[PDB]
Amino acid sequence: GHMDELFEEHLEIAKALFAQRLPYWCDVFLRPADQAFNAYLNARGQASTYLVLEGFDPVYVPRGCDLDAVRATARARARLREAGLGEDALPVLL
Amino acid sequence: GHMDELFEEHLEIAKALFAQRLPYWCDVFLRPADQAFNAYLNARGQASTYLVLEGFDPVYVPRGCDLDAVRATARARARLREAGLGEDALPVLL
Ligand SMILES: [Ca+2]
C-alpha cells in the first residue's frame, strides 16, 4: 500500500481522539515511519508530541493532554498487556 | 562493532544523568538508532521515556523527571537553535 494513504487514514483516527484531547496509542508503523508520523500530524495541523513508553509502547499526544498522565497510563497498560489483554482493551488515559 | 561501544558508553552517561532525574538530550544517534537507544536503556534496567516534538533533538527522560517540563524545554531549545546557538548552550531542563 501507499504510505500516503496509510498516514492519511491514521491521521483521521488521530483527529477523532485529539478532538477529545486524548492520546493516540498506535504501533502499526515500522521504523522510521513511526517517528515520521509525528511530523505528519504536526504538518497537517494536529499539534502532537511523540512518546515511546515502557520501551515499546508508542503514542502521539495532542497539546492539551498531560504527558505525565500518559506515562502513568503506560505503566498500567504494560501490566495489562503482560496479563494478556489486547491493545483495544488497554486504557487510553487513566 | 562501533554501535555496541556507542550504546554502552552512552548508557553510562544516561545512568549518571538519570541519578539526578535529569533528561539526556543526546544527538549522536542517526535516526532510527535514536529510538533504539531508548529501547536499549529500558532493556538495561534504566527506565526511560523517549520524547520527540518537531525537530531532531533526541531526548531520554527518566522516571521522576517531569515530561511536561521536558516538552516545554524542547520548544525553547528549538527556538534558541533557530537563532544560531550551539547545542551545548541550550537549556537541558526549564
Ligand atoms: Ca507534569
Image (cartoon, coloured by chain):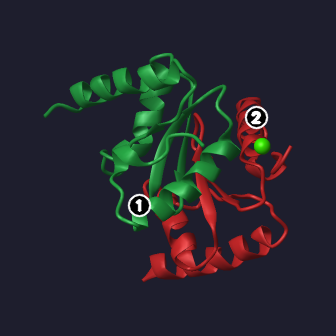
Chain colours: A green, B red
Residue nearest the observer in this picture, B55 or A14: A14
Q: Position of residue B62 (x, y in %)?
A: 71, 62
Residue A19 position within the rendered picture, expressed as x and y whole percent measured from the top left: 51, 17
Q: Position of residue A46 (x, y in %)?
A: 51, 20
Task: Give residue A81's mark.
Answer: 1
- Dot 1: element: helix
The image position of residue B9, as x and y in percent, is: 62, 79
Q: In front: B87, or B10?
A: B10
CA distance for labels 2 and 1: 45 Å
Residue at image x 66%, y 44%?
A: A69
Query: Which quadrant: the N terminus of chain A?
Result: top left
Q: Is residue B7 left or right of residue A3?
A: right
The tag on residue B84 is 2
Can residue B58 be seen here? no
Query: Quarter of the picture for ligand 1?
Result: top right
Q: Does B91 sit above or below residue B18?
A: above
Report helix, strand or loop for mark 2: loop
Of B40 and B76, the residue lying toward us: B40
Of circles 2 and 1, the one toward us is 1
**B38 left or right of A35?**
right
Q: Is residue B23 above or below residue A16?
A: below
Tell me which amino acid carries mark 2.
Gly
Classed neighbour count for the residue bearing mark 2: other residues with Cα under 10 Å, few (<14), some (14–19), many (≥20): few
Query: Is residue A74 rendered to the left or right of residue B88?
Result: left
Mark 2 vs mark 1: same chain?
A: no
